[PDB]
Structure formats: structure tokens, C-alpha cells
Image (cartoon, coloured by chain):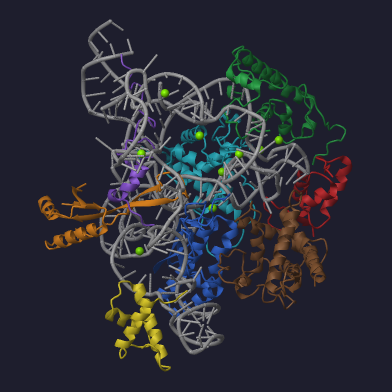
Amino acid sequence: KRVQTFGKKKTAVAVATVTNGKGLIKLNGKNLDLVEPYILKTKVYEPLWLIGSGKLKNLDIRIRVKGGGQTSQIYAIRQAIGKGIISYYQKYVDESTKKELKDVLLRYDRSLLVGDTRRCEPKKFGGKGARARYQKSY
Amino acid sequence: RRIRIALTSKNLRAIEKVCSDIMKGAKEKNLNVSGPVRLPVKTLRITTRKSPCGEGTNTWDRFELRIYKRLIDLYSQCEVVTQMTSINIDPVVEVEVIITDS
Amino acid sequence: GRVRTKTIKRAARQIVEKYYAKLTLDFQINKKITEEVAIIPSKRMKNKVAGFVTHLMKRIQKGPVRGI
Amino acid sequence: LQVIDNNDFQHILRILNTNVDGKEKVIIALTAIKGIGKRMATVICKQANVDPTKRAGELTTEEIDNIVHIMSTPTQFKIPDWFLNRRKDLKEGKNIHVIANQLDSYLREDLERMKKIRLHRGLRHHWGLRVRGQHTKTTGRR
Amino acid sequence: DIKLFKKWSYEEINIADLSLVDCIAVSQKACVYTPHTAGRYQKKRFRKALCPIVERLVNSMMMHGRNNGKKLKAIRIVAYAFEIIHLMTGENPLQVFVNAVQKGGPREDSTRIGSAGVVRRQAVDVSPLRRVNQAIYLICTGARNAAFRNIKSISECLAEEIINCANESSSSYAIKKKDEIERVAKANR
Amino acid sequence: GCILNVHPKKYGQGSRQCRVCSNKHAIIRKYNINICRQCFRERADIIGFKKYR
Amino acid sequence: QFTEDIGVVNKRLLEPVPFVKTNNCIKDVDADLFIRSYATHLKLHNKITYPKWCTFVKTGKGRKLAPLNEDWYFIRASSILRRLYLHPDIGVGFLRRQFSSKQRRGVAPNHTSLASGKILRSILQQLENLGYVEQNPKKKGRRLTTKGENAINNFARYINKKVYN
Amino acid sequence: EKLNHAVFIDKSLHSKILECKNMKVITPSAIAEKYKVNLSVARAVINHLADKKLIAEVCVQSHSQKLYTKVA
RNA sequence: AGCGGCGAGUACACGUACUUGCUAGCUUCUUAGAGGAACAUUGUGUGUCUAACACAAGGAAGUUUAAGGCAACAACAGGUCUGUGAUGUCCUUAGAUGAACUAGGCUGCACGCGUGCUACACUGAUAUAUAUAACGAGUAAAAUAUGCUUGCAUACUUUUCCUCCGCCGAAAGGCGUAGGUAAUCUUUAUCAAUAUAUAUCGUGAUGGGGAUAGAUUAUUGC
Ligand SMILES: [Mg+2]
Ligand SMILES: [Mg+2]
Ligand SMILES: [Mg+2]
Ligand SMILES: [Mg+2]
Ligand SMILES: [Mg+2]
Ligand SMILES: [Mg+2]
Ligand SMILES: [Mg+2]
Ligand SMILES: [Mg+2]
Ligand SMILES: [Mg+2]
Ligand SMILES: [Zn+2]
């Protein structure tokens, strides 16, 4: 009937809600077609093509996003979609099929299921950044 | 009668202990008590230079003063709660009682 | 590097000497035994002591170990 | 597809006195006159009903006359007061917009007038130094 | 049924050198729809050889300070260059690019070796990873220098450079620099 | 008349000073501390500030 | 109801997608296409007037050149209508922050700038005469009427049916 | 070595340009180098040819690259 | 703080988007307290098979997982008496080297040196449009109103900090009025610019660059 799973990137967080339905996918009230950087749309479409169309005719997905930037929001949306489909199959369908689908996604790539731990480094006094130092003259 | 108890303090141990004591003391009287609300912690920062004078490598140090805050609701009388509040609290925590009837 | 200071090694060696009949070749059980026997304020140092205890117990199966 | 004849395209013009106005587009070709920037070139071209997407070498004579008319006395048209140079003139108390040649004479006269009175800024023009408060101990060093 | 840029297959492409087969990646994990993957490829020594080859191309394509970190602009440049490559000499542009990668790095070089205090400039041998890296770097530098203060666009320059590199023609930057390296190497030992 | 201390001193460096020394340089005005930097570095612990990193 | 012409429809809009769509509101249409098409509609039906004094202004401090399209007024009006549908109770300060740019200060570094206010206020008052926006009595700012939402949504649906046939 | 591109089309050159429809890679740079004209002129002639469907699009163009091809 | 639940609508497709009154339960998202988790675990190799190192698998994580704070014994004639009602000695103390008031200088320009900002363009400039952050801050004087000839007596009843919103003005800004001593308002399901899209320019010290100068207009402040 209903699950809720998140995906994360640098400081972006996306939450996907999955219910039984008729095929609709929406993002902040809008169709997925209106995701903004057109060149990065394939990344959002990837998990769907892998899992396919027949298994996904009966589901309806709503996604909210918050924080980050262009690229990080795209990556969080991918991860949330993939984890949400896996979770829905784990909660309402035999979980041998859950294992099969998880293997397909993991064969393509991780970070469709596993978060990325990287994070901006604090800067220290004596230079513009975390590593760079002011120019020394003698 | 929708009385709110508010606690602020610099010390984490102190305010945590006071909150625990009030929570347990009000439950001996069989009262509807709303669990503590821990508001965001707020930090006061000063970044000053060492070196009274001006020579040598330029080094700094970063100072921090952070403030904690708890919040408890319950239905009771004014006299009961004002007696329960005051048992000579560790005087590093501030306690104030307000009636939120609206 | 992951070299163990003398405090860790001395504590592990005494633990092995005094409680040999209980100890095993599994890290989690030995972690629990070390929690119960000794006094270690930090869980990190406790993990390292238990790890060396297990490593020492493995060596004893092969023959004599010097200092125990 | 324009096929303009090679014998009617004219390469050097003389719009005001002392101008050339080559093979450029109208907006940029009008900026060779000594007091026409990009903003006012655009506005003037709009007030003369001339297409901005043609080259200056294909402007007829009537269009040139209309533009030259607009450059003088531009308050008869709808150009507001805050587009102009010389908004009170110190001499006649009017809003005027000075153009080529005329502009150089006005600059020369301002400098010599404030140098005749022994004003500080005019005297620093006379000595050849910066006049707007700049430090001048490490820069400006030819 | 995964295509590069949704047009080109690389299901039939081959290398045919056998020294560079392990060092260029068009296979299971490296078949992608777009050359953007935010992977961790520099944490270990040899993990660089599993980054897909077109993504390494786009990674060297954003250089000289003005253009640091501008990844999407590089991807657009590379995609339109591949369209231009396919239009003329109609083939799979990825196959042409792989052929050019195979040709643009020197096979031997020179260095200072301290045999017995007295030294030389002895010839040495180049490893496959070194050759792949040098090919990529020299192709990108050739295209970048061609388009500076020039009427032609950056993707036209890149298409021309790749096509010329694949055909061994001595009008490309990479081929001539590599020939000079090999000549000096044959001279100093 | 008198001309003693008659210049206007409502704003500027000449208006405020250290709460302890009476000096007029490097005053902390954030949160209304109003102590110059040296005295504050001496008194910060008892005031309530700490060094963590 | 609508017989007007739709602007140039570029490709990359006709790609097949792996889910199913809807179209009932403007949250279902592309924004650039809607903006240009409805701007032409407003110009053609004389629903708003180009203030005579705008023929010689620029749109902000930071610009230092003029818009150079001759249709910029209607385009900004249609963007404002769509924005009002996305954010109900909006003032003129919000809109000044909304159309910001960057200002190059010569040999000094760049900073963010802010748009003007007369253009924005005149457009809002204009749309108030037409009965497409109103001033929330209880709240602040201003929002859409029922007429405004109905017109905008009907045009969005018309555009969507036009594109995908 | 300074370029001397013309900024407009002549009667005599008019016949000459329209053979730009009978070749493979149609980019503004190629036309400019071939016929020694401006780049605005090359963009305008590309637009004229594609308005009348005498030239085919190879792909989805962008604001920065505009390649075409001869008609099949 | 959110989500959800119950009603009334505005439009569409035969449920979706938005507005709105009210308020079963829940903690995914937000916040913050207590705990847990990695030990080189397992496999394979090198090593005296010790101390240890390398690769693969699993795993959120395997360079002590990343960054910081703390900093032994002994020194320098290192810097600071221009931080100090910390201080020894020497000067000076009514025509003061004390304390103030008016104007000026610290910024003066043939030149030499260090840290930097902006550039030399098309992987760009200009103009429109679309999408998108994190750490912060914020309330004794002067000022607005009767009797009197620029001054007095009067409320410390308003105001002084961030300022939504409305109106005026090309713009800078001005006038009138809310909220807020703050997870409550400014203001952040968003307070930026690199990005992305479309058009113009077209290798020309050029629509690159923006120094140096002329004129007019506002605000802080005696
Ligand atoms: Mg940096
Ligand atoms: Mg200097
Ligand atoms: Mg903009
Ligand atoms: Mg939680
Ligand atoms: Mg002293
Ligand atoms: Mg003085
Ligand atoms: Mg100085
Ligand atoms: Mg110039
Ligand atoms: Mg410029
Ligand atoms: Zn002090």
C-alpha cells in the first residue's frame, strides 16, 4: 500500500513515496519531464529502464527534493527512486523477486542503492582553503 | 490548565538532571505530562587573536558558548506546579512558568 | 600504522594468563569477556585489547608462545 | 535574401563634421561621433524609425538627415533630461547635449576657467597630477 | 541496448593491439548512456583504468584555469564533436576514437640514469597506462590550441584532431610530438 | 564661558572605550561585550567561553 | 475556443518517456513555450499596454544595456502570471529579488544586483484592471482571481494538446 | 594575413553561394572559409536554405553548434 | 517541527494540481538525548612466519575512517612598558611632556620592494528566460507634540536594531504603516553566482578591457 524511502547527496535529500496505482510519477507536483538540466535526465531515467515497464505499471511515485545543487539533486533523486522500488517489493511481494531486482540494480552500479559519504572539508586560518596557503616571499 | 515549563542553561548535565527530576516528580501525582521538547542548540562565537602585540605568525583561537533549552507541558493548577518547580534547584538553570490558554 | 603500545599488550597478556579456560577464537565473545573482567574507560581501547587477546589465543594452538 | 549592389554600398561616410562611420552596423557605427555611446545610439536609432539590423553603408540621405537632426536639439523628441550631458551648463542654465568638436572646446574651456581662478583641482590639472583623491605614491608611475 | 549518447552501440568495437586491451574500458560496467559518473577513481593506484574512456576524454577537456570544473560544457562539446565525426567518413565515432587513442602515445622514451656516477640519457620503455594517458593529453592539447583565436569552434577542432590521429597523418599534434619523442629515444640509446 | 569637553562625541572611536582598562583600541562590540581584545582573552573562561577546536 | 498560433516548438520535447503523463494545470506544461506563446496572445488581444516611458529604460542597475526585443514587456507579464500561480501572496520586493542579475563593477569584483520597481508595479496594477489579480484583504501582497487561474490553465491545456498531436 | 571577409552578397556571388547546398558538412565556418564571407552571412544563408527545405538537419542543434547536410 | 485524517471549493481526466476551515494517529523527512558499530574481521600472498605489510570479499566506513584542539626537558638578551589602577629607575609637573578647544598632517611624488584585484576574448561579450545553497545577525542621550519671544517649561506617553507590505520616483532613494527581545517575524520547501536554453555579434585594440577625465542627482554626518 505505501512506503517512504530517502536518497542523499552532498546536502540534498529526496523522499519518494510509493503506492499502488496506474503509472504516474511526479516531482514537487510536476511530471518528471520538467527536471531542469536536460543533459542529466538519463541519470534519473536509468533505474526505470533497468527494472522495466511491466513491473512498474501499478505504482505511483511522488518525490520531494530539498537542498544541494543541480547535480547532487539529480543523484539523490536516482537513489531515492531505486531504494523505494526495492523497499516496496520487500514489503508487499515475495522477497526472492526483491533479491533479483536488487541484483540487477547492483550489477549496473552502486550509488543506485548506497549513499556517498564525501563532504566539504573545513578551512583553516592561514590560507584561502583547507589546503592552500598564502604565498610566501622570503 | 495548560501550564508550560521552560528551562534554559549553559550546562547539559544540570538541565538534563532538572528535567528528569521534574518529569518523575510530576508523574507521582498521576498527571498528563508532555515529554520534553529539546529546541535547537545555539552557539555564541568569538574569534580573537593571541599575541598582545603584533609580531610573529598570525594565530587565532575560536571560542564557544552554547545554550540549551527544554520545554514541558501539563494540565494542572498554578499552585501545584509552582510548588513542584521550586525545591532549591541547582541555581545554574533558569525556570519560568507560563499559562498558554490561548 | 597499526602497532600496539605496551599498555594494550600487557593488559592482553595478563587477561590470557588468568582466564584461559573461558576464552575462545571469536572476537565478539572475547569482547564481552574483556568488558566483564578488566576496567577500561574507553570502548576503543577495549576493542583493541580484545583483538590482541584473540590474536594471542590463535597463536597458542600452533605451539609455545614466549611470555605467557 | 539581400543582394545589395556593390556600386551603391558606400564605405566611408561623413555624418557630423570630423567623422568616418565605416562598414559597421548602425548602432556601433554611430559610436564614432565624439558624444554617442551605446545607450544613446540605440535610443536615437529608435527615434528615427530606422532598422537596427542593417549596415551604415546602406542608409539613404533622408535617414542621415533625420539622425543628424535628432542628435541636435533632442528635447523636441521624447528624450528625457537624464540622458544628457551638460544638464545646467553654468552658462545659460539649460539642458544641452554636447557633441563632437563642440565637446573638446567645452573641456578646454572648463579646464582653463578653473585654472584662471586658482582652484585646487584646476591647479592640479596644471601640474599634471590626479585630481580625484587617489594616493599616487606607487601607481601612475610612468 | 545501452548506447552512448543514445545513438552509438560499442557492442562490436575491438582494440586489436593486445597491449592496450586491459587499459581501456568499453565493457560491462563501463557501458553508459552519458559520460557523467561521480565515481571515486583515484583512491587506488590502478583504478584509473576502469573509468570509461569517453569520460576520461571529457575529464581532460576542461583545462587552462578558465574552465575548471565545468563538466557539462565539456560533455556538450564532446557530443557534438562525435556527431561531426560520424557525418564524414561514416563509421562508429567511438571506434574512430578508440583507434586514435591507440596511436597517439609513444612506445619508448629517454631519461637520466645514474649507472656509475657518469650518466646518460638512456632509452627506456613506456607502460600501457602511460601511453593511454599521453594519447588523451596530447589530443586534448592539440584541439585546445587549434581553436584559440580562431574562427572554427572547439568541437570542429576536436573532430578534426581525432580523425587525423586515427589515420597516422602528420598534420595532428599528437602524431608529430610522439614521432619526435621516439626519434630522440632512438638517438640517445 | 567654558570650552572644556564641548566637541560632540556621540559616535566614533572617541566615544566608547574598554570596560576594564579604559583604552580605546580593539573593542569587542559583538553581543555588547565592550571589552578590548586582551582583557577578554584573559577573562573568557570565567565569562563562559570555551576552546573546543 | 482558441485558434491562435503556437511559437516555434523545438525538438527534445518529443522524446518518448517511460512513465505516464497528465495535463490539467500549468504545472504540466513547459515554461519557456508557455511564456512566449501567451505573451504573443496578450499582445494580439490588446489586454495590456506598453507604458510609453519604457522605450528608453533598462530593467535594472546591473544591466547597462537595454532589452533589445521590443516584446519584453508582455514576456515579463506572462512570466509574472505563472509565478503568481506558483506563489500566491507576493509583493513587489519578492519580484525585485526574483529578476536579479550580476553587476560588473569595473576593476572591482562582482556582486549580485536587484531589479527595478516601477515596471513591476505598473504591470501588477495593469493586471488588476483586467481582473486577473486582486489584493488579499486578509493577507498581504496579491494573488490570482478565479478568472486568472481559469484563463491560464485553459491556455496551458491548449498548448499541450497542440504539441503532442 | 589579415582576413578580408565581405559583409554582404553580390549579384555575381549570388549564384556561387547556392552551391553550398550540394555538399556534406554545412557549418558556418565551412561556408566562411569556402566563399570568403562573414559568419553572419553564412548563418543567414543556412537559415534561407533550411526555410525552403533544401537542406537537412543532422541532429538537434544547440545555440553553439549548427551542422547541416545535403538533401538525400 | 512535519506527515497524515475529516469537510467546503476552483478546474480538468473519468484520479491529478492548487485554495481553504478543522483536528484518528505516526516519526520516514526536521530537531536532540542515551546507546551501538571496525578489531585488520574472513580468504590469499611477503616477512626471522615474530613485530608487521599488501591485495580481494563483505560492509555506511578498512591510509589508527576525515579534520582540528592540547602540547615534555632546555633555550633566544626574539616581540610587546603604544592593552592594563602590572611594575623598578630616570625625566616633567602652571609659559606642563597633565586635561582640553580650533585648524592642519598621518593620503604629500623623478624612483625601488612584498601581498593582491581586474584583464588580454568565441570553452567569449550583451539581452531575455528556466532551475538551485550553507554557516550567521537583529531594540543616560538625542529625537516627534500646548504657554511664551533661535531659548525655556513639559510623556522618559512614541521613536533609535532587522525590516514584510502599500504608494511615489529611470534609478539611487523617499513617504505611510505591520510583525519581531526571536525554530514564532524580517526569512530560508529557500536569502547567491558559476550552470542551462534561445537570439545578436564575427577574429577587426573589435560590441575584448575599463584606467583617466566633464557635467548633474541622492543619502550618513555638527
Ligand atoms: Mg577555494
Ligand atoms: Mg605596488
Ligand atoms: Mg538573469
Ligand atoms: Mg528520524
Ligand atoms: Mg603599559
Ligand atoms: Mg585636535
Ligand atoms: Mg599609514
Ligand atoms: Mg573598444
Ligand atoms: Mg566591454
Ligand atoms: Zn581592556
- Check the image and report above or below for A4 versus B90: below
Residue at (83, 64) in percent of width and height: E169
Give the chain ID for the orange colour: B
Give the chain ID for the yellow colour: C
Picture colour for chain A: blue
Picture colour for chain G: cyan
Q: Position of residue H26 (x, y in %)?
A: 78, 54
Q: Is residue C19 found left or right of H61 in the rendered image?
A: left
Q: Position of residue B12 (x, y in %)?
A: 26, 58
Q: Position of residue D39 (x, y in %)?
A: 64, 31
Picture colour for chain D: green
Give the chain ID for the purple colour: F
Q: Is residue G72 visible?
A: yes
Q: Position of residue F31 (x, y in %)?
A: 33, 42
Picture colour for chain H: red
Give the chain ID for the brown colour: E
Residue at (71, 30) in percent of width and height: D31
Which is more toward the observer, A113 or D98?
Answer: D98
- Check the image and report above or below for E9 versus F15: below
Q: Is residue A63 visible?
A: no
Which is more toward the observer, I62 or E69?
Answer: I62
Residue at (63, 25) in percent of width and height: D129
Which is more toward the observer, D61 or G155?
Answer: D61
